[PDB]
Length: 255
Ligand SMILES: Clc1ccc(CN2CCN(c3c(Br)cnc4[nH]c(-c5ccc(CN6CCOCC6)cc5)nc34)CC2)cc1
Image 1 (tube, rainbow, N blue to C red):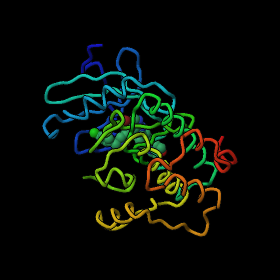
Image 2 (tube, rainbow, N blue to C red):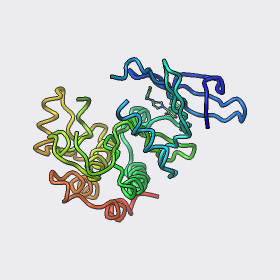
Image 3 (cartoon, rainbow, N blue to C red):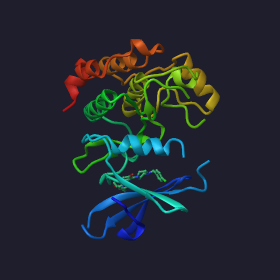
């Protein structure tokens, strides 16, 4: 509907941002609890936001954070979001230092579903990472932040860690961007850091580009294999989500 700031009691900040802020909040009439992202039209310098709104508003899936509405204020702008009671996968990762195969395989599965769904609408997220992954009340994973997403195919800096060769190289990309990230994520869940970390934007580039990762000895054949299949330079050689969900190692450990 037509919305407004005074429909809502603000509560705690949930995270900082250069574009704005996200508060805990409660719609006054329903006592409905949600996340309000409040943005600064001043810093913005329109383009993706229109997109991140159009796209998120039109997606409903349990593993994808809901967009309920927006409204601008004209010094500010507000997205009314689903609030995710258990925080980010990123804090969960930093708290527990690394994940068992079970947690990881499950997360990946949820992720696969949400992604498969997205591609089924020709939607590429392009920025799947822990800080954009959220936990519902059941501990269910929830893809968030459709800030960089677009229709496929597409063309296009910010951190390089979860982006694929085809994208950093400025080539043309499609839904397969997400498949490379699922692999980066898988790795990072198991290991505690992404397979191309480096101290330098420029070095991480060379790593991503030449596809250079090694595994800790503690990483099983089953995961090595999946991760290796996910992380192929030529996007066409990456498995469909359907195969991903099928993978022996996935099937052996998810829920
Ligand atoms: Cl403008 C802007 C500012 C910050 C951000 C980054 N944040 C974006 C996401 N935010 C949340 C959104 Br949207 C929806 N539901 C949420 N729920 C939480 C959440 C919930 C609980 C916590 C606290 N932890 C709960 C688990 O135990 C340890 C403490 C921290 C965050 N954050 C969000 C918080 C993280 C993005 C954009």
